[PDB]
Image 1 (cartoon, chains in turn red, orange):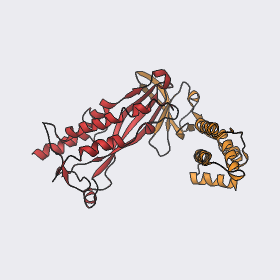
Image 2: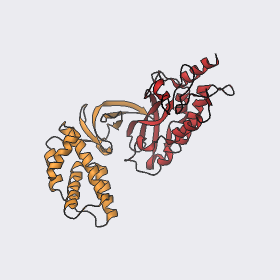
Image 3: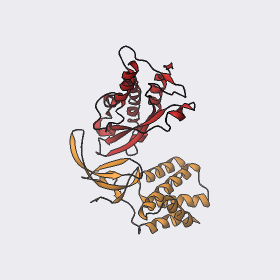
Image 4: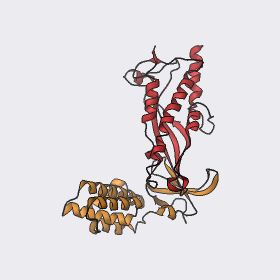
Length: 184
Length: 158
């Protein structure tokens, strides 16, 4: 079925059950690894590196029901394990940080956006995951070229992955992607 | 120099505990690190063994370094810059370096002002942040809660 590939498109796009090390360079993992690492500075000055280890997805605040009986979304928070390394001193600081909330499919094949049981569609051969997985790549693009802008206002000893990162650019990237979608 | 289970401090994330010695290859160069785990945090730090003081790592206060800290909060005085810009710079440094003794002595001075002459909010935030940090390292050292470590401080002032 059309809806079968899609609930699978999305399925492996996420690898949300795969042990990160057993996760493959596909979709989200691809997006992450394409984006990361981010180097900046001349190595000597504030020579920096922000690198990706893995992402985790923390299960949704509510099951289908509650996201439904409320003008909100069936979402899971997504966090990623990052390391900041000073090329100067060799110190690594590893935080898990929150990047964005992330919408989930039903076995039916739909999302509960702001309560609305909306629907995205397979275009130009691209499937659900793919079309989305590239939107992921977008936010991350925007987020890099952030992180690396912060990288050059100094504060080396003060800096942390946490401080290089916020949730806005990825929030936006999926905000827009899902404001362009059908209503079942 | 440092051993697993050692309670430690690493500016800026503060107190932690040496997990063990980690071997990471990072950017094509494999090296040994001390691994530091942070409080209910999921955040870690990896410090090269070759020189860890060099990079800010230190032991935390022993339970017997603690009463001297409490005396600093109670009776501590230090000279501070005339002008607010330079003063905030000094305090900003003291807070960053993470020297508990220097921080306690600063905090003692700042609190003193808060009483006699009055403390600017800007400087007040330096005091709070100082308290915050000291309460966590004292809580760690005596294995009491942070709320409990603060309450200690509160009494040291009256």
